[PDB]
Length: 265
Length: 265
Ligand SMILES: Nc1ncnc2c1ncn2[C@@H]1O[C@H](CSCC[C@H](N)C(=O)O)[C@@H](O)[C@H]1O
Image 1 (cartoon, each protein chain N blue to C red):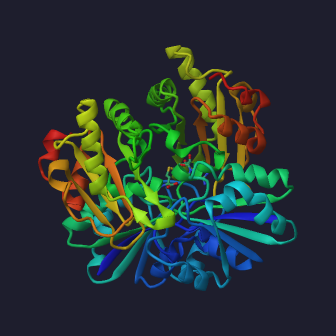
Image 2 (cartoon, protein in one colour; image 1 turned 135 degrees about the vertical axis):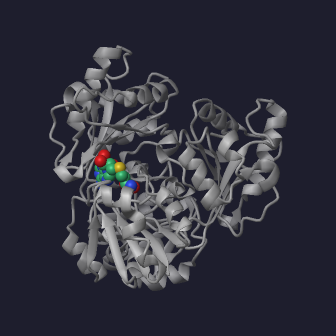
């Protein structure tokens, strides 16, 4: 009679919370989805071994089209778990699944876990100063979306930081690197000429958040555009005007050039 | 030989990540602070039992003034952990403590935990639509803080949602309720008269996120300002322009007035 949305965390199988793990172990059936994102630091097998239950993976169609036919039926006479990378419901479409549960007469509970949305706090930048977020999507064919560029402009104009989620082709396990994102942004700038993203723009790259050894680098596009930030996933941030304390952290912890203390503060 | 920043999570001792627990259990010394937030579902004893170590609790003064004299010295010859509610680097100044660690020759690592900043996803509102965040602080003496009012105004003008962290006076066991936050906002409104926060403003309240049964309520200030949302902690949200799906969730899950379904595109 109960459905549990359980978050898996940032990177590997140990990023789930103790609460999530224990609940998952007591569920009769355990489902999971890896289309909204991937758990780059582990494998389905390792997650299964930790939970001690076989995990049935669901595709985007399985969920968006048949959630009420695949998952909910079992939740009627059993405790069912639905695992998702990060924190449940941080992905825009999963909240509606709670409504589906309701109309099916199934109780649902959410077990939270760390999300890159909150993990960016490790960049040393004040979380309250992050504005609207955006996703840098790979262009394709005659389609060249650029709304993420406008988001940076609007945030920066108000002295706010911009968190940029990078595109991912989960099915094919293809990660967009911060380098590719920087190249795309420069391309958009050349098209729009808004003076929003250039070689002189200060950016911050956070790679493999959740890991004990994430890569945290800060600096100007001209210097970081071809730098190796390690394996995915990568997150890109365009800070607004920095608080001195934010800048000091980027310099001392993220290897930012001393120049940011007088140019970006 | 190292210092660990480990989050404890939203509500109880099981909100710590498996990663955080396994590491905490192997540290030689464990410190913690419980003034940045409130974990309403646990106690020091239960946390100690789970980790199997004695925990020395530090006050805001111990940390901000003497972190390098109380914690860092031991981290030079031992494995030390510093525990905090939620995520250690979200809506705190703990990030700066990493700078102190570096300058003291101590390597530090961060272990994330669920944060209220991302947990708001359970309100059904799109995470990317949250703009700048703010804190509603208790007036003191002749001092009446009001900056949070301007944050709401700036976000709303952009159609963005506003997350409002509520004040806390740990040593006095005072946890600002959503009701008190609403009362303060109405007073600021009377002064600035910007039409930002009135009895007709739609707001969302999330209390005790992390628990299995958090209170999630949406409605007009006039109706919710005297409603009982249960024990603290609470956070207040002022939605911007709602998506249909956002409104649908608030109605179905948060008991919001069905009239908000009719969006004024
Ligand atoms: N479980 C919870 N439910 C509702 N609000 C919460 C909460 N935990 C924290 N808050 C809110 O955030 C304030 C503390 S701010 C510190 C937040 C913490 N680093 C984190 O990552 O969550 C509280 O006063 C309250 O307004």
